[PDB]
Image (cartoon, coloured by chain):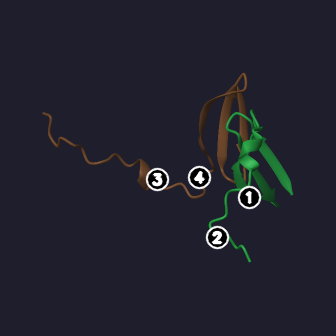
Chain colours: A brown, B green
Amino acid sequence: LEVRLLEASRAFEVSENGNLVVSGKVYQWDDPDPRLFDHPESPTPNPT
Amino acid sequence: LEVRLLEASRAFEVSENGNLVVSGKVYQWDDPDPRLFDHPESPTPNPT
């Protein structure tokens, strides 16, 4: 599996045998926010 | 100028000191046909 990164555009591409398999965008997280990982409000407040 | 290619995605970029400059898609023309380059009929005759 071959991985190529385009630093300028923050894009990546995984390829096998010259065939595209995965694509998207990846970049370093500049300022992590612990608030992000706080557990969200439960859809059902009280399963009980 | 630095140019990187992703044959799998047929995408390219041109970066300048780590700054994106140009982007898009480029690939070899599989089946050229001269009929594409025939001059389209002019909307205005312009006879004079």
Kind of residue sitting beneath label 4: Trp
Q: Earlier in the sequence, mark 1 or mark 2?
A: 1
**Element at badge 2?**
loop
Q: CA distance from mark 3 to mark 2?
A: 66 Å
Contact between labelled residues 1 and 3, with CB atoms less than 8 Å apart: no
Disc 3 is attached to a residue of which chain?
A
Q: Nearer the viewer, residue A13 or B26?
A: B26
Q: Which residue is mark 3?
A: A34
The residue at which mark 4 appears reads as: A29
Comparing marks 1 and 4, which lies closer to the viewer? Answer: 1
Distance in Å between CA atoms under marks 1 and 2: 36 Å
Report whether B44 appears left or right of B29.
Answer: left
Subunit bearing disc 4: A
- Give the image quarter of residue B35: top right
Left or right of A35? Residue A9 is right
Q: Nearer the viewer, mark 3 or mark 1?
A: 1
Chain of the residue under the numbered disc 1 shown in the image? B
Residue located beneath label 1 in the image:
B22
**Nearest to viewer (mark 3 / mark 4):** 4
Identity of the residue furthest to the front in this view: B48
Indicate which label's residue lies in the foreground, 3 or 2: 2
Same subunit, labels 4 and 2: the answer reads no
**How far separated are the C-alphas under marks 1 and 4?**
25 Å
Which is closer to the viewer, label 1 or label 2? 2
- Where is residue B26 drawn, in percent x and y? 74, 45
Residue B12 in view in this figure: no
Local SS, label 4: loop
Q: Residue at x 68, y 56 (%)?
A: B40
Q: Residues within 10 Å of mark 3 (few under 14, many from 20)?
A: few
Q: Residue at x 74, y 58 (%)?
A: B22
Residues flagged by tags 3 and 2 on a common chain: no
